[PDB]
Amino acid sequence: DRLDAALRFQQEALNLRAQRQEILAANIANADTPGYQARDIDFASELKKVMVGVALTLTSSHHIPAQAVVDLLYRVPDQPSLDGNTVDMDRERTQFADNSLKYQMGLTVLGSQLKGMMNVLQG
Amino acid sequence: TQRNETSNYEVDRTIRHTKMNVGDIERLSVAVVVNYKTLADGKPLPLTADQ
């Protein structure tokens, strides 16, 4: 559908921001686990990958339709801890706040596009 | 381990429509009686098992 193509980029950006938000909050929650590595995703490359499948064929009514079913990069440690935990509070707190801001911005842009498509139709 | 398998099949199909004939035979029973054998003398000699 053409409607999907217009809203594909912002939807994928919003979903990627939510996933990275979950990853950052997981990094915050597991700050005290000894031996836990701080993981993160490269937002731009994954957004390229998602932006850049074959529903199985249903011959009749009984035939069952096809059933549907990111890469994590390690953060470079800054300070060496003794328990092997590489999670840094300041870095991930700033990243968490930034991801929240960008999620809000994506919501704003997507809502503006939908509202414009709506006022085009209203009449 | 996780295996999710979905398969759609096409099957052979045979429809037979039959209208039985009216007047067919269900059960036949037959009674046959034979005579004896009267020779030139005239004695009614019975038949044999083979015959």
Image (cartoon, rainbow, N blue to C red):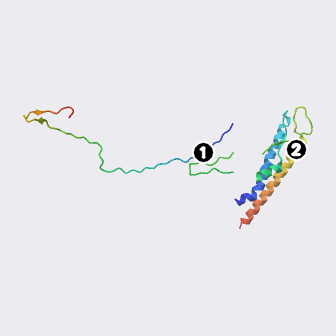
Label 2 resides on the chain identified as A
Q: Is residue A28 left or right of residue B8?
A: right
Q: Residue at x 89, y 43 (%)?
A: A91
Residue occupied by mark 2: A93
Mark nearest the camera among 1 and 2 is 1
Q: Residue at x 13, y 35 (%)?
A: B37
Q: Residue furthest front?
A: B40
Label 1 resides on the chain identified as B
Q: Residue at x 78, y 55 (%)?
A: A10
Residue occupied by mark 1: B7
Is residue A55 or residue A93 the one in the foreground?
A: A55
Q: Are the residues flagged by discs 1 and 2 in contact, CB closer than 8 Å?
A: no
Which quarter shows the N terminus of chain A? bottom right
| Cα separation between marks 1 and 2 | 48 Å
Q: Which amino acid type is shown beneath numbered disc 1?
A: Ser
Q: Position of residue A113 (x, y in %)?
A: 77, 60
Q: Which amino acid type is shown beneath numbered disc 2?
A: Arg
